Image (tube, rainbow, N blue to C red):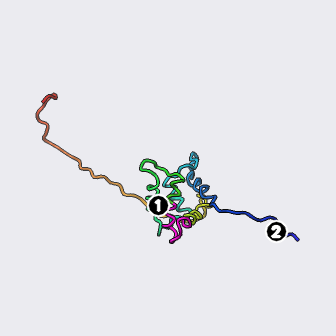
Amino acid sequence: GSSGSSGMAASTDIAGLEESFRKFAIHGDPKASGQEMNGKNWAKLCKDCKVADGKAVTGTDVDIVFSKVKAKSARVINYEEFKKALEELATKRFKGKSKEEAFDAICQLIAGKEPANIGVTKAKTGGAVDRLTDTSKYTGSHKERSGPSSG
């Protein structure tokens, strides 16, 4: 008779979210300590973690949220803000779940998941349009009279 040997434990808190965030936060960046997260990584994190399905949550929405949590000054976001975006993409991502449930649901997508490459195909080529109206002023006959300054 062997019978099971030990087996028990509890878990109320996520305990993995902030762990994953840091990863994506310091994604590649060896200098990154995992205190800040660039919108480029944030969005990505909301991609690899399959947080931004694209339907309910669009890379544009997350982009806005990311710029809605941070400041026109700051360029990165902090966990505090990060979780804020998740909250906005929580009810926007999931159905009509609870603020906590939805948030915990979106966390269940990150918490545990890593920014690792992961053998998965998903992306979409995208560019931008540049331009700038150039009035370009041109004169011919002007500045006839001469003077030092006093006039």
The picture places residue 97, in percent across and down from the top left corner, at 53, 70
Q: Which residue is mark 1?
A: 62
Tell me which residue sits at (73%, 63%) in the image.
9
Could you say which disc has been placed on residue 4 in the image?
A: 2
Closest to the observer, 83 or 114: 83
Closest to the observer, 66 or 141: 66
The picture quadrant where one finds residue 106 is: bottom right
Left or right of 33, for residue 91? left
Circle count:
2
Queried whether the magenta region covers residue 93, the answer comes back as yes
The picture places residue 109, in percent across and down from the top left corner, at 58, 64
Quadrant including the N terminus = bottom right
Left or right of 57, for residue 139? left
> The residue under label 1 is which amino acid type?
Val
Instruction: Report the magenta residues as a range.
Output: 86-102
- Distance between the Cα atoms at labels 2 and 1? 47 Å
Question: Which sits earlier in the primary sequence, circle 2 or circle 1?
Answer: 2
Judge depth for marks 2 and 1 and give the one in front: 2
> The residue under label 2 is which amino acid type?
Gly
Q: Residues within 10 Å of mark 1 (few under 14, many from 20)?
A: many
Q: Main secondary structure of the magenta part?
A: helix
